[PDB]
Image: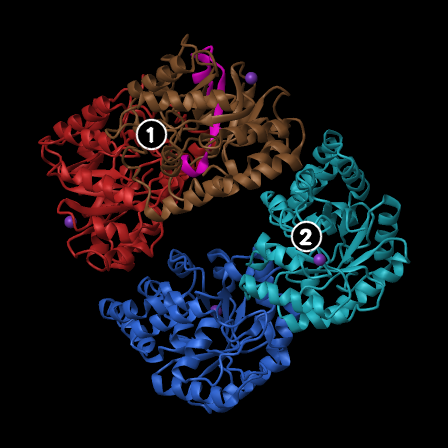
Chain colours: A red, B brown, C blue, D cyan
Amino acid sequence: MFTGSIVAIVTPMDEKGNVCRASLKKLIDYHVASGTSAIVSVGTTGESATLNHDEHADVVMMTLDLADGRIPVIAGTGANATAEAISLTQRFNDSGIVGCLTVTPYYNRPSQEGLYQHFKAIAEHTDLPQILYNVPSRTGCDLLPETVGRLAKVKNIIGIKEATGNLTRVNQIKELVSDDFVLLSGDDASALDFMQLGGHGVISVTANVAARDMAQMCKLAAEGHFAEARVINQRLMPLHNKLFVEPNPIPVKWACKELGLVATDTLRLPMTPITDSGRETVRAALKHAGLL
Amino acid sequence: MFTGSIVAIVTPMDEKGNVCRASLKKLIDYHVASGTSAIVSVGTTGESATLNHDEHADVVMMTLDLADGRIPVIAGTGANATAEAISLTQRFNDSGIVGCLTVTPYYNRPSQEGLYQHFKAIAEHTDLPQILYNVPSRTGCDLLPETVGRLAKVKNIIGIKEATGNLTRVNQIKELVSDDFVLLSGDDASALDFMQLGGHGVISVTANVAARDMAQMCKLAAEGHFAEARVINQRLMPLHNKLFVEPNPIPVKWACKELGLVATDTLRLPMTPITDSGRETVRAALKHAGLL
Amino acid sequence: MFTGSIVAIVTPMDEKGNVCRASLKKLIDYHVASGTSAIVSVGTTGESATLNHDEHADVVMMTLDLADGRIPVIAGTGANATAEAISLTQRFNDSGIVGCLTVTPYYNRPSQEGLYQHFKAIAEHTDLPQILYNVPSRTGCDLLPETVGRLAKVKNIIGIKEATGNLTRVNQIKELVSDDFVLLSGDDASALDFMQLGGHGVISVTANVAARDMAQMCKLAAEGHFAEARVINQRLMPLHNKLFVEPNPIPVKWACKELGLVATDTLRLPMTPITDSGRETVRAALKHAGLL
Amino acid sequence: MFTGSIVAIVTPMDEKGNVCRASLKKLIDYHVASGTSAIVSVGTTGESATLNHDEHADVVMMTLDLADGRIPVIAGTGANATAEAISLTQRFNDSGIVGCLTVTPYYNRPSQEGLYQHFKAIAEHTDLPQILYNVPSRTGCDLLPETVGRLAKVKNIIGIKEATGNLTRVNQIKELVSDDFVLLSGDDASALDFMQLGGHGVISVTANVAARDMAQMCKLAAEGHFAEARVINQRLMPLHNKLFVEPNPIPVKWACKELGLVATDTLRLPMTPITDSGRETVRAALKHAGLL
Ligand SMILES: [K+]
Ligand SMILES: [K+]
Ligand SMILES: [K+]
Ligand SMILES: [K+]
């Protein structure tokens, strides 16, 4: 559902840069078998940036189709134009998705009032649950706790993917919102800390390749067994860091390929193939994780 | 030119959020009368973010028609997917624009090699002169001097709009590029300094409302009359700062309207109307510039 | 001892800027009565910066004398010259203090290896327990977890006052050190979070004026009653922030004065009297805390 | 002068960590022969941090004697307590030094008003010309242009050593001060740029080992021959960078020794001997400068 280990799933491509269905199916089967709570489809790790909205929609539909009710699917729906965000959302009305992950507008750097108006308008024109998404390092702006608090009063704004890696934000946000509001980490390396502070889960890059460990860890964290969760986390930590040694999803797509989870590690420009140096850092991380 | 004062022109809109031709014509006549060297159409200040590519192309073509051979027009062509950058650039091939202003991919944060491959592919699918554009605060990435040097070796990559505010870049880039590679400021408050270090002009937001002073100031600069240029700069400096008191282009659109240069200060969400406190700030800066 | 609520105690001065004994006595009595675990004497809040080592020693001796065994006293001993650090430490051999709080060298910005050698040398030439102190915002350098880990193997380096407000440091450090090693917050605003993540206490500015609440909160945190601790913390939070509205200890010394805890709020230059604006922000914080 | 190339001279030490007179004399003769404009004695590069005030005064007086009227000598007088700044400055009153270099209080992070009161009190207890010194990365505080403007109104406050690396400050300060207030770079890698914007010279670490080129370069700059100056700057640029490959003055001391300019590269803890990897880096930069 909207807690636990949620995978920010790669969009597996062939050598032409087109979605590879066979590979997506394997990945979905892998997640159903590994205890992953939900799949975020065509988020950042999903290369939302370089799929056009038609392809973005296909991949979501294909993901849902392959999932076949076995695992909930959340659609990435973010756009830096509110009209575009709205209109992309409509595309997934009645699709079967359980909700949407919607990023703060990138590049144009709106005010807090602007972010409020953006997200309120989007929530207005759908019945689907909305997860807010904050990642200033990508977007150039920062959705502050106060504004999260105003937006949480809207019926179908139900949570936030907090990707700052600033852990003070957990309780600043939490004080300000009801206990039903979901607090999910968007930063693998600090996600166990995030959960220990009161977070409910993680929308994860690491889960693409360490699905089971991430699921166990997140469940331990929810039960208060932090010591036990850390042991897993310790072992995943090089992966938490080195999946970003080169721009996400370059490392993780290579990792999937190396595990045999996807046929090719192809991406679309401006993402470029992994360097040999990166190959060697990632492979070492995988082995530390015990995955290789 | 690709020297002197270049306006990053606002896209004036009617109350419905669509381009207002009467207001655009006024603006262009003004820049023609004021001695502005060129117009950048649908760059950041032109709200590229909230126009779709058709609307963007319409505004560019409308601007070109209205300019009527009197002043060169540079098309904003930025896009964070390389395929989309190519496709948008292709819309203007054999159109009469004199060049493209193309920004580093935002949000997806490519490597330097990715930046290289992005812009190289773009350059290769056009005869148009290309001006690179670096604005890390909006994009999440930083096109370093070295990559600039690499890209300057491509025939139709002929300049950079440097919006970091970091003046050390002028001479870092200069030493690595040829004598005729153009260096333009993207930061009004430091543009004169930029020019004094060896930059060749500015793509300016301030020029929207103080086109005459800006053209004056850059002429002085090119002729090496910096003390003189500097008297104008201090006249404009509060505008250089306070045009960003709220997110650009919210302040400059209000200022245009106030100066009677455009009919309405309407913008597209997620940009929001200027606050009362913001009006008063901007109006003060305009008084200081001698424009009210 | 070296856990719980530990006060970074002000050095109360008269109008000549000289230690006011009557005021220090009141403060010490207040801490013994309020359940404060220990007193840090002549730390940062204690104006170590502007007391010469002779005065620094007096204040420590006078604090110990007034405490009269009722409350443990830790001496600030930090110096950016290792010889000086050593020699200042010798001054407190057999004094009665239970330990020393020693800051990373300020201004000169040594390497990690330098910090290792600094702290190892100091620990060598005393039997007293040493608490490391990291606060990059003041010092210009950052003692990283890895180096904390090497230093924790030295017998009498027993803990760290981590003042970064970066909460990822708690478990990075903790993984690397034995379970006996003490992890204390040096940042009031994030101290409950710090403790929730595995910290043992706080060396606190807020404790100067909210001794009892801070003691209760820290004890709740140690017992795992985080929800109950947060309620207190919520009420102290404006104080956690506004005691730094102007440079520490300007606000807190004024606060003490306003409570009647000290006779004058005098400081030594380059610390300057509180502004009226600051007066009003602090008084509001105190009232929110219920202290006024 | 207080213009041209000014060396921030190393305090050469014997193997015991005490000033080595033979080596200091060599250094001074070299600067006299090389055309260095003035010597700053016991500034940051001179290890002010690890010398007590007597030792500091001894080195200053020794430097003055050895200079023997051949080259002006500026005493480092910084101190984070105002009383100590006054007392150290008083040691040099009627000594033959031509001015003091006095840094913003480090560690205690005063307000702008505190900075004002600090330096004003200092100026008032001496007839010596005072050069302000801003280096936020070491001190934790930033003396803004406006406060500089305020302080320039004091008679014996006559200049600033600006070590931010932020070139915008040259013209911000300049507009607020009188025509004869001196602006010196504190950042070798940007000093030529600093000068091209209107700065009057540099207090340099590079000049320790490339005194001749540095003096050449600043002459060219003052005469407005920037292209020419710039050929020298690129010859020195790897040294400008790699002299900080490890904490200053670890690299420049090793380089002096290597050039036979001093007997030993010994420093005081917490500064540590240069790493093997550091030697090789620095030696490379020296080869590039044409000095090996
Ligand atoms: K809600
Ligand atoms: K070119
Ligand atoms: K130990
Ligand atoms: K003066």
Q: Which mark is residue D269?
A: none
Q: Which residues are magenta?
A: B118-139
Whether the magenta-drawn stretch holds residue B124 is answered as yes
Q: Amino acid at mark 1?
A: Ala
Q: How many C-alpha atoms fall within 10 Å of the one at disc 2: few (<14), some, or many (≥20)?
A: many
At horizontal 85% and vertical 61% (from top left) the residue drawn is D64
Q: Is residue C249 visible?
A: no
Count the numbered circles shown. 2
What residue is disc 2 on?
D161
Is the residue indicated by label 1 positioned so its CB lies within 8 Å of ligand 1? no
Q: Position of residue D35 (x, y in %)?
A: 85, 45
Q: Measuring 17% from the left and 51% from the top, which residue is drawn there?
A: A153
Mark 1 = which residue? B49
* Relative image position of residue B217 (x, y in whole percent): 58, 31
Q: C123 or A17: which is nearer to us?
A: A17
* Residue D89: image location, x then y, percent: 74, 68
Which quarter of the picture shows residue C124?
A: bottom right
Determine the image quadrant of residue D234.
Answer: top right
